[PDB]
Image (tube, rainbow, N blue to C red):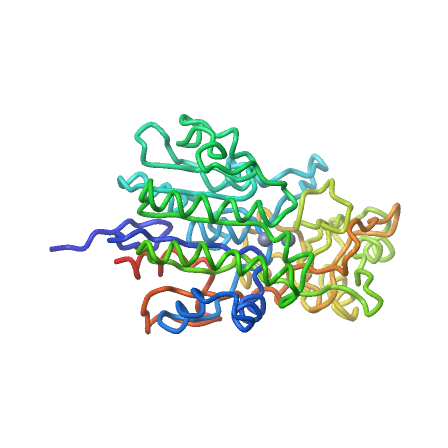
Length: 413
Ligand SMILES: [Zn+2]
Ligand SMILES: [Zn+2]
């Protein structure tokens, strides 16, 4: 007898005999789990690690939320699926255009491919914009798909989400967007879906709210992972094959005095090339954001026609804190990104620095606590833990976070 599989974006996924789950722990620097385990707070993950397969994996660069979630969802890098930031800039038009709409997704998700093959599929996110992206191609007329966010759980309908009011269904209020509870809702929905819906494929993804605010091992960080472990214990107890991974890690990005440590790329380019001759883009978040949530460790820049790219790159790389500077072609090959949605040059900052645009009218910082962020090579390493014996499972740099569903269904088969 031939084995059953689903082929998606050039990869063959065996059909899962038991439910196959990937959990994306947003911003989960491996140190978070080590600290919580060491404090005795994750007895289930501790045991799961001992008896399963424990690895580190590499995220996509940029180590941002959307590109990495979409990579996990499609099993492919952004060169394939097209989502490589929150927005891009169009030199013609002079327009900044949001890349977080499903129309910009260029490759099918694993979720749609399994759904189209007759599977039961469930996707739960914390934020609703990612929900719409992740849910592209799912259908809700056969009772075989569920897709909603904690954020808009009370707005779910049968026809568009596969469930009527997921808040009422789960029996928990809609959580505050800026809370651990937004992510707890996802875990809780996941458990209830596993019991009652019995998906063949399920993705659970959260937000990095806690991780931007709190370093590994501090009480609030430990409490979050203590909470996760309870849901993990339950998913594991119900017999699912589970991969726990992350979209990206998290590192402190502040000076000794606790203030943000930023390299203002637009200021530098204005000086060398003329004011606004170039455009620096900060794709970590939406373009309107100026409140320190716009500070990450990866940036891209669009340069005036004719200028000396090679020269400009050398000038940027000479700056302390700027670790990597690549032209479009090279950055796209190295990081597996789409040339048509990346700037002329790509910049990656050092471990404890971020990249900003300018101090002209500035980038007024919001929250109090010392800056923590992601986007660079120093937030690329993430946990990758499976609750099954898989001695052949590769390790980083070969293992990618977007191998999560490949190995989950393999373990489930
Ligand atoms: Zn994230
Ligand atoms: Zn973040």
